[PDB]
Amino acid sequence: RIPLQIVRAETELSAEEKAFLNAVEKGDYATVKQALQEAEIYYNVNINCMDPLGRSALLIAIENENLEIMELLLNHSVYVGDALLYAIRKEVVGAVELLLSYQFSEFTPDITPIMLAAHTNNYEIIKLLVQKRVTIPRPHQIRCNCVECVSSSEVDSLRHSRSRLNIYKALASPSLIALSSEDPILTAFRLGWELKELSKVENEFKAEYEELSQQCKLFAKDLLDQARSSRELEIILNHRDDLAKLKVAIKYHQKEFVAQPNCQQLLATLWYDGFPGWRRKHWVVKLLTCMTIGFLFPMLSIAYLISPRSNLGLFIKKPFIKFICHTASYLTFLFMLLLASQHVQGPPPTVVEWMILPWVLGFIWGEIKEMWDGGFTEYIHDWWNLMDFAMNSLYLATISLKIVAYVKYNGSRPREEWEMWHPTLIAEALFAISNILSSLRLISLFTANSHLGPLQISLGRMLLDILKFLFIYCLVLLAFANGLNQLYFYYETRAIDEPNNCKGIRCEKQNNAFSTLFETLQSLFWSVFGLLNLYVTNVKARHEFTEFVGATMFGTYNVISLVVLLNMLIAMMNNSYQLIADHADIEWKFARTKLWMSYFDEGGTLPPPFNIISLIQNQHYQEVIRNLVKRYVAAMIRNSKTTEENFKELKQDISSFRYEVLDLL
Amino acid sequence: NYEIIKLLVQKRVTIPRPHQIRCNCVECVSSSEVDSLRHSRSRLNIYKALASPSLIALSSEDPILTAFRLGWELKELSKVENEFKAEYEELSQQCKLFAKDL
Amino acid sequence: EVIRNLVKRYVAAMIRNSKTTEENFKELKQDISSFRYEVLDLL
Amino acid sequence: RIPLQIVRAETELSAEEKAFLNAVEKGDYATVKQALQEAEIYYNVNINCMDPLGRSALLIAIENENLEIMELLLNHSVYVGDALLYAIRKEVVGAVELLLSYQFSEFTPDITPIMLAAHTNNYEIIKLLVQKRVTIPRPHQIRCNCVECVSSSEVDSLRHSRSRLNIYKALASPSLIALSSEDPILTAFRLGWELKELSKVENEFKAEYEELSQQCKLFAKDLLDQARSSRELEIILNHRDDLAKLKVAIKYHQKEFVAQPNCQQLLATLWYDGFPGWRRKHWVVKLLTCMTIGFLFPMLSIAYLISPRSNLGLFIKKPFIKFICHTASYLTFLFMLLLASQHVQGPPPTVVEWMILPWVLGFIWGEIKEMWDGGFTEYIHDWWNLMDFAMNSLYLATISLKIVAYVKYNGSRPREEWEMWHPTLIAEALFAISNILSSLRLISLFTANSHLGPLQISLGRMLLDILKFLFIYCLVLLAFANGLNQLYFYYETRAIDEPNNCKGIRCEKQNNAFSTLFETLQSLFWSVFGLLNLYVTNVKARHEFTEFVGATMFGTYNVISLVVLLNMLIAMMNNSYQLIADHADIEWKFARTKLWMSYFDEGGTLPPPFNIISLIQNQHYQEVIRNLVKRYVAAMIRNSKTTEENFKELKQDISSFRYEVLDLL
Amino acid sequence: GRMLLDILKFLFIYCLVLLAFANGLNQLYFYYETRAIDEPNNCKGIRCEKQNNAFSTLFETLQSLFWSVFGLLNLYVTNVKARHEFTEFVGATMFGTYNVISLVVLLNMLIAMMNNSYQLIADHADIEWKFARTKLWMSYFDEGGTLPPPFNI
Ligand SMILES: CCCCCCCCCCCCCCCCCCCC(=O)O[C@H](COC(=O)CCCCCCCCCCCCCC)COP(=O)(O)OCCN
Ligand SMILES: CCCCCCCCCCCCCCCCCCCC(=O)O[C@H](COC(=O)CCCCCCCCCCCCCC)COP(=O)(O)OCCN
Ligand SMILES: CCCC/C=C/CCCCCCCC(=O)OC[C@H](CO)OC(=O)CCCCCCC/C=C\CCCCC
Ligand SMILES: CCCC/C=C/CCCCCCCC(=O)OC[C@H](CO)OC(=O)CCCCCCC/C=C\CCCCC
Ligand SMILES: CCCC/C=C/CCCCCCCC(=O)OC[C@H](CO)OC(=O)CCCCCCC/C=C\CCCCC
Ligand SMILES: CC(C)CCC[C@@H](C)[C@H]1CC[C@H]2[C@@H]3CC=C4C[C@@H](OC(=O)CCC(=O)O)CC[C@]4(C)[C@H]3CC[C@]12C
Ligand SMILES: CC(C)CCC[C@@H](C)[C@H]1CC[C@H]2[C@@H]3CC=C4C[C@@H](OC(=O)CCC(=O)O)CC[C@]4(C)[C@H]3CC[C@]12C
Ligand SMILES: Nc1nc2ccc(OC(F)(F)F)cc2s1
Ligand SMILES: Nc1nc2ccc(OC(F)(F)F)cc2s1
Ligand SMILES: [Ca+2]
Ligand SMILES: [Ca+2]
Ligand SMILES: [Zn+2]
Ligand SMILES: [Zn+2]
Ligand SMILES: [Zn+2]
């Protein structure tokens, strides 16, 4: 048998205290009033006694929404400490107004009435508290190093972290931002950004800061959703602290705000400046119009160069037209690259190369102009710039090596006897790599398309899982390469001994697969695709044990890399894709908005190679914001209106009515 | 709500007729240029009203054919209207389900 | 006539399905309080 | 503008009829009574008038659970047609008892009060109706061909199908089976089986019959769940209309009933007859005990043969011991098969073959004994028997060909010059195929294991999707084989012309890949695994267009079969596996129960090759069933107890109370 | 790590299939075993430039069936010097059935299992990781083992 008792004993209530608490719970006003009046004379009942759950009479009255018994207890001067917090958490308006006019706790000591009200996100109570003079402490910098912060962190890390989280929960309240905020949209943007930064910094409590940031983002999107006319939307998006506020939203990665339907509709009307009815057109009509504009891109560029003020001069400044012209220019560049492959050491550039050169110069000039104008952080935040930098550097190296070979060689020697590191060979290799990168650069244009955009977003996301798997794969590969090279480096053979004077795995009969570490890495790589034959694990000597051990290392590597690792990669990608699919549209619309806005600026109008040849505004914004806040508050109250405590309140009301009727009769 | 809809249709009430999906009259382009948000909202509200299963149950000679053609038109609008695509899709699906339930 | 029968049946079925929120509890509290005030005034 | 009017007009209510219906809705008893009394004298209000929703006064009273107004309307003789159906569907006890003591409809004409009550599955109302003399029509056979069935089907298929579904919904009611059923468990078993058969037959309404069958299965499982002692469970499982009822449940594929925890616990206690504490033992102890019993299987078999009544004679009749002995016997058979491969035309059988022969004879004798004892349908329902039949036939063919080669050949001729269809070669090929099948037969033992059982169930399920994909793959394969053979059959070359006198794709240099249809099918098969080289699409003639077209056919086949079809197969399997995973345990426990019960019988005790050398019972069952039904009814009522109409009823009660108080005051 | 359990579970069924087909192929082909001298380069087995004797012995048969999983076993190893076209066809059919099972059926079933298991684990991945990292951190809280090798000796 297990004896069961009370390990942590407490002070039990008396019979009368239990009867009085039961009367308070049942809502019988008459008996509670009689007990309160008798306690003043006889002092037999402690009006501040708790219950087995820790609640006092005032807490019971608050929990039952019994304003009459609550006020009766307040008129008899019961202990009221922290009762305001329970009233605020219960989200009962009568209790807060009753207590505002005047031990164990469920609330941490740093919780204040206004902070708790902001946590509940209850507009009525928050407004009641902000009607007075209340303040919320300002959190320090995310990476602050002042004496107070480090002292509080060292004295009590848990308390300090809890207090910071409570403050940020209060500040991120949509109702508290609706009131007491000059610019709710900008406040939500910057607060969400700061919460995301805190989530990055705070390894723990990461989920809570992430959800607070998401809540701020949704509040900004919902404020934008309350706009009822295009005039209001234009006023909001163009406000300066054009499309200034839209650019600010893009800076803070407010994807839901940017992808809002009305914002996208306005952006689309700006995108198709020339064509008023592009929305309602057939596929063939759109394709023919695009082909015509693309084929006429050089004419539009020349017209802009000569006279910008004409039917053709300013026709290229339209964003969709500019995008078409730039795309057509790049397509012609790629076509010339393809044509460029249809004994002189350092030959002069051909006609195709002479035509290619201005495009390369234009690419370099455009990149450096973007660096000079936009800045450094903006330039780096665009990943494509990395590929653009690689392409430009490879092209510059190609030109340099071509010049070197032109001014250092004159004779015409057959390529068979050229040096391995001859400048022409290196130049051609670099040019071929640049061609690959240039053709691959077309991926970034998938953003412009409805069917290819979200797919590109998804594949981008899956590249992160692929990179994560790359580390473990490379560790395994290096391990087995070390083992195989250690086993086989004794049997290295000269190229002369080979049947065709060819050494390595790129010969018709593969050999010396594991003789050197570099060759071993290549062999293990090519075995992933099955291009390494099994006889490479064989040696001329009759060392059958060595051959078997090498074959077993090779087989274990195959099993791991193919059966285990590749399938695990499929499972990871399969799962990651499923996660991303829900957000694919929002993510795509954000990326497409960035692409569209990149064509709104005056700079960079000409594609290569042609590029080398306040008070009233605030007032309007304030009135629009006031309307938006009213609409949002009404809508969210309606949504919340449209628990066991409700049934408890219903029972309390019925019992109070019953006791009143019974007493009256 | 069938009761309230019936109460209002007991009187002489009308709902404006939406223009063609690819209409190019002066009124449509004028309203689109003056206020695109208001025009799009009004069109969506009208189609939400018309696609109501209760409003099709009353005030419709052939509820099945009305639901068929209204769902088709809503699907076409969903194709044309790049934004608000989800709302037109769900209105079309609602009309299809109403026909199936009839 | 077949369509009339179908519409009657569909309306009845959908009303039944809908019949089979916080505002409901607010309405219940409102009814109870109105009854309480009427009784208190009468007595 | 769209004019909106009432296309299907109706008869509007008068002002007084609307006021009276509003009074009924609000529950004001006094005004409704006054209106009813005034209608008798002045005839100004139609007491049977509908509302805009079609409800009359009685229907409104029923829907609000207002028994007083309901009884008042009944005392004034209002129209009552189909009101009982609305009362039953509302599941209100007072309304049913009120109406039992005494146009458009929401219920089809075939619905009767008892049928609707069974549909609601409400025990109180069903009991109230069964207290009288009520009957439900008996549905005909699933494949009945009488005159009435075909006449009703041809006259009105919709009405007939609806009536049949309504009848089966009534009969499959757990409450209606709890009452009015001699044996609820057997009734649920056979009714679920019949509903599953109807679901197969009825292509439409398949989902409804499937869910009715599942509901019956769950009712049987829940009745078994109410057992409170091992005596009750034994009485239930052993009842005969041992473990008779468990065998009946297995026959009707009642997987949830068989897999119930207490049933599995009892079966486990029967399974480990010899070892009382096998449940609590270490892995090493269990493994050592299994190895010992398995190594001693011949001793146990001989002991059973000599004296069945001894410590060793009857030790093999225990189910787990018998399973271990049979498994060890099969393992030794496979070990001898492996050993059997460590110039005489038709040689005499070796020592290993002489040892193998009695095992084969034992397998054949055991199969024919199972066929003779169990029956034909039971023999066929076991899929493994198909593989057993194939193994036995291949072994018999092997023995026959060995005999033929022994009695038709005496000389010792080298195998190089033997005929292609020499009896010894065919015998060896058949024996090798039999060895493959025999070793593969061990899959069926995965059921016995906790970790391998559910996995085998899942792979079995995935074999159905693989078979489904097999049809489309074979269609594609046949199509492309026809095309490639048509293109290439002109360039067929003789084997002499080949470099090594080898023709076909199994040569070191593959050739004639598509010369014949049979060879083309094999080539397309082996290209799935990449074993067909690309040069087989080349011909000696300089027909570069023909070669290119053949290479394009081959490439399109590769793209389809590998990129498209194989990935689609992965998606199907991936999805099917996810479906099965939830039911994997129940399915596995059913299969393991079948395996365990197969070792409960006296017949087949000896493994190969040693096999070739009532009123009181019903009363007890009835009392146990009565207790189970009481417990199940109480439990399901509790579960149901633990909608907008509830709030409507609350408002109705409050308003009725308010009107009564106001009238009294 | 979690997916390694599903891989181990699949290992048993794969090994059963592999052993079955190795027994069958070795039984069929062990009559045509040839000496290493008869080979073109005095090399016997599947690790030669021209593969041979793929199924002559059980050990070699197991290795051949293993390497066919990665496609490194050529199809001509199912050919014999004698003109026993029926034997060659039966051996090629055993080899093809093994390929179909192990690659089309078993490998895809393994992908489905891993795919499902990964989805199960993903929810608990963080808690599980933090437990493991806590164990790693606590292993460095003790005085013993402060010096890493070779300074610990
Ligand atoms: C010694 C001999 C060597 C011989 C080598 C010969 C072959 C060379 C060919 C190498 C191939 C490189 C492949 C790069 C292709 C990148 C394609 C990614 C496209 C994609 O779906 O994701 C987008 C990637 O954009 C991006 O982030 C930018 C994409 C490119 C970034 C990386 C640049 C690749 C090239 C780097 C140098 C290579 C030199 C070659 C030697 C989305 O992402 P998002 O930008 O919208 O992100 C959002 C906010 N973060
Ligand atoms: C001309 C030359 C030819 C040369 C050929 C050489 C190679 C021959 C080798 C062929 C390989 C056959 C593979 C069969 C393996 C079946 C394994 C299935 C195991 C599995 O997971 O599913 C179980 C299958 O049981 C079952 O349903 C029974 C499994 C076996 C049924 C099919 C029998 C296979 C053999 C048929 C004849 C083959 C002759 C070979 C020429 C579960 O299912 P469950 O029973 O619990 O179901 C429950 C109620 N339905
Ligand atoms: C990330 C860490 C993962 C750890 C996983 C480890 C698994 C290692 C297994 C290495 C398994 C490596 C097996 C292997 O080298 O043969 C080749 C060697 C040399 O020719 O031959 C032998 O080792 C002799 C035995 C041949 C039978 C191989 C048994 C096959 C077992 C599993 C195959 C699985 C295939 C799946 C379809
Ligand atoms: C079930 C029905 C499914 C229908 C699907 C049809 C797709 C058919 C495509 C056939 C695609 C067949 C392409 C093909 O024979 O080359 C080989 C031929 C002959 O040597 O060469 C050529 O045809 C010349 C063009 C070579 C470029 C091939 C372009 C590749 C296009 C797609 C490859 C996809 C690979 C995926 C990673
Ligand atoms: C775990 C148990 C699973 C049981 C599954 C069994 C399936 C066994 C099928 C064996 C299928 C084995 C087919 C096969 O040996 O050819 C090779 C043989 C010998 O060269 O050639 C022939 O058998 C002659 C017929 C060639 C046509 C093959 C038909 C292809 C059928 C299915 C291919 C599926 C590929 C999927 C993309
Ligand atoms: C696919 C193979 C044959 C290579 C062909 C190279 C190019 C000819 C293709 C590859 C990607 C294509 C681009 C993919 C993305 C788009 C977006 C597309 O924009 C739209 O979808 C219209 C709506 C809009 O953007 O306003 C304009 C065509 C374009 C540039 C495509 C132009 C033709 C491109 C460059
Ligand atoms: C796996 C490779 C190396 C082939 C080896 C062949 C056999 C030696 C293996 C293959 C499958 C194994 C069987 C798989 C299933 C079981 C169930 C197992 O039963 C239990 O799990 C104990 C609990 C119980 O069944 O009561 C008894 C061992 C046995 C027969 C195993 C015995 C050993 C077997 C036959
Ligand atoms: N260095 C480079 N900057 C750019 C910007 C746009 C572009 O067109 C494309 F179609 F590739 F996206 C090509 C390039 S290359
Ligand atoms: N023809 C055959 N009937 C049976 C029944 C059980 C058995 O043991 C195994 F371990 F394979 F399941 C083998 C066989 S073979
Ligand atoms: Ca750039
Ligand atoms: Ca059997
Ligand atoms: Zn600080
Ligand atoms: Zn118009
Ligand atoms: Zn009949």
Image (cartoon, coloured by chain):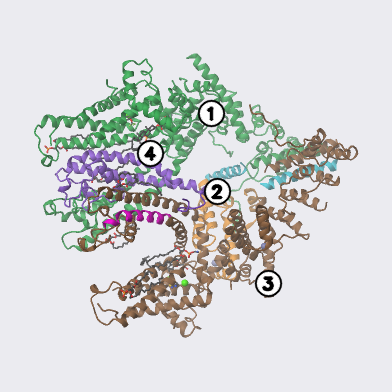
Chain colours: A brown, B orange, C cyan, D green, E purple
Identity of the residue furthest to the bottom in this view: A306
Q: Which one is nearer the viewer's eye here, A126 or A233?
A: A126
Amino acid type shown at disc 4: Gly
* Residue position marked by numbered label 4 in the rendering: D460
Asked whether, in this view, residue A569 is left or right of residue E141, the answer is left
* Classed neighbour count for the residue bearing mark 1: other residues with Cα under 10 Å, few (<14), some (14–19), many (≥20): some
**Circle 3 sits in a helix, a strand or a loop, which is it?**
helix
Q: Nearer the viewer, mark 2 or mark 4?
A: 2
Do dots 4 and 1 share one subunit? yes
Check the image and report above or below for A110 versus D161.
below
Q: Is mark 4 within 8 Å of ligand 2?
A: yes
Q: Is residue D211 magenta?
A: no
Which residue matches tag 3? A618
* Residue position marked by numbered label 2 in the rendering: E142
Q: Residues within 10 Å of mark 3 (few under 14, many from 20)?
A: some
Q: CA distance from mark 4 to mark 1?
A: 29 Å
D63 up-or-down from B85: above or below: above
The residues colored magenta run A472-491
